[PDB]
Image (cartoon, rainbow over all chains, first blue to last red; front, side, top):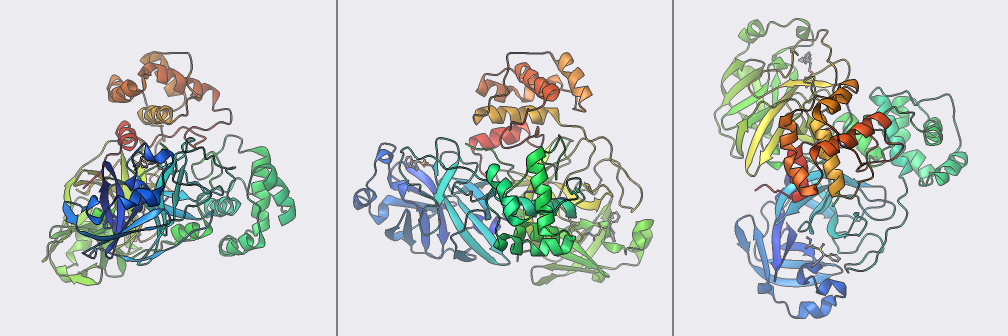
Length: 306
Length: 306
Ligand SMILES: O=C(C[S@@](=O)C(c1ccccc1)c1ccccc1)NO
Ligand SMILES: O=C(C[S@@](=O)C(c1ccccc1)c1ccccc1)NO
């Protein structure tokens, strides 16, 4: 029993982190097979980031200008190319620690773990969600660019995020491993604001199910509701609209607990309308939305990875 | 910027986890050099745990009764012994993945990372604190015993916790790596209740400093206080008494922010007396106490580990 914000074990990713230096700029890269992946703004100076022409700036760079260091060992760069907003650096040595992996572009509302790194070295691991406005609420300081976000299924690491920017509001933006930004953000130091940070309704419901499984049930009530009725409340409180697809994904948690999805929606509705009256739910005084239904099942059942 | 509940990278510990089976009981062990460490209640059945005599139950066990498996490979047990509440199983092969490590017994209020494992396999990582009542609020299911808690300093893993029990209230108890329980708990299925769960005042203050560094400053006020005056409030709200030693440890955070420790105590005092009026602090609607001053400095500065 107990429910915690849990990250995947990070070892398989730790073995992939390297340091990339171009000129006077140093950030992190991801070494998979004989390719190192990193943000293309490694080639920029602080002056450049105001209005960079990446294609023009890359013309002045050759293989030997990209210094790649894995732990204490230097890797030989034998080719380089730009794909969207990442660079791919071909090296002469396949990473012997390459895990089974894939590249995935995730949807808003999905969660992943982040290995924060500096100078190619791991600093910490934590769990995040892709917000509905395509930012993430992370913990990133200067030099953390190139750190990546990932999920694991048994033995396969699914890389879904590479860190690129910090917006002026303190939230974070980045790309998939093909270099396409999440959301409308660009790798330019300009005026880009985040949209509304709406709450991920299906994740809150899954967390309420997690609560019930662990003994926190004071919020269960005598009511039920319908999807349309609940969604009128969701709109008022800047919650994502709940669909039948969401109801279907919560089916297994409904089955294990015996609480119909729409009955749990009626509990959530009362919590949004009345607040929590100074009580807590799984140690939290607000409604948590960065656990997916899969996350809840996984933690409440003890799935492992070899 | 941003502040997250962050765990240490777990790879160095992942490489130490093994599976231990005695009879029909399977839990996790920790393989360091040529010794595997695990809870002594691996030798018990469910019937035994009501009133076990561990010395008598061990007499019926020989080296070949302890089955130790690291990944897919079986380890040869060539000796075994009991130390307090852990067993030490000598094996014929030193773990090649043994990190630099030490065994440490931590104090209440100190934080550590937990690698939850099942059947010797890692499941997830999260951050915990040793509570003032010597429990931890974890996430542990059946089969998680032997999972361990640890800190890392550059290249040295300091093991401080091994998981042994779940109390009837859902909180968790366990030992250091010498097998001595934290607090008054015993490896018996009897009536053991936790004491008062007091809040770790020095950690809350450090987290308020973290908040200020990241732009959340609405709770700063015009007041100051004294240690004795603040502690009258701490007592009322079941907070740990604040000492000069605590004030001294917060010195560096005081210096970086320019906010005197006693001024931050006066902010905390108003927050305890008035609540947060529906606002949040670093994404939380209550006062977080599982970040130490060291944790705050580390995350706000980007310390790494090689
Ligand atoms: O190297 C860093 C600083 S980077 O965030 C920042 C940047 C600054 C100088 C050179 C390259 C990039 C930037 C600016 C605009 C848009 C995205 C990123 N972190 O690791
Ligand atoms: O094997 C497990 C179950 S264990 O928690 C439980 C126990 C049950 C059967 C055999 C050994 C131990 C126990 C009971 C009383 C005090 C501490 C622990 N988890 O990994």
